Length: 233
Ligand code: NA
Image (tube, rainbow, N blue to C red; front, side, top):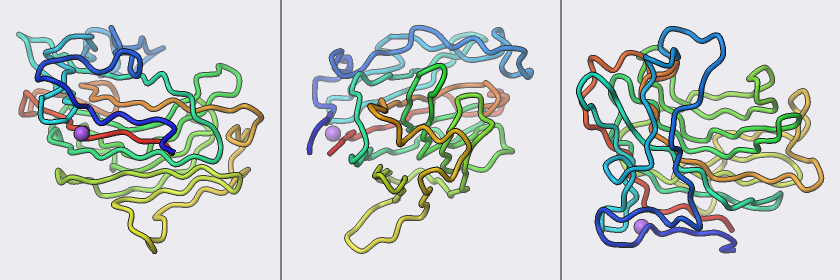
């Protein structure tokens, strides 16, 4: 380490580093969905400087906007593939804890047969589900370990350490801090994270609507997610 880093430096309105990040050009199509996952009800993703830009103050801004009756936001899919024996950290400010918003900082292995997902910072604007941290052994969501974690609008560092022994999560780490969650290896059915050559890509998004987002009618838009850095070492 650092094996991967992005400090998000650059002039205001510029785009994130295209060698490091690929912005979603649309919101994923959900199968047989709940109301707020219906395609006409979800908020869309655009690779647009109105929704994903650098502020010129060394933050990535992911901003939800309302344009007429439709909502738009951003999702960054990182190119870096990191493996077992790495720590992943993002410093983030959730200026978007409002109705409809569904921001997240997470890690993804997209393998259809053995994929997995580590959501270390997730907040639900649907006014129902508690914010928290989730390890997903299966992408279908049927084999997981979760821990609700209060999430406010202050700056926080969110950390995951991935070792052969499992997954460790810290909020605002310091030397001597005990992890607030430790998910042991093989503690989940179909646990994939100890497989040969398993890699995880860093992900950032502010979704609007969808199941976790809910109805954005009551929310204050525009709404912003700030990312000072993402680092892997
Ligand atoms: Na920065």
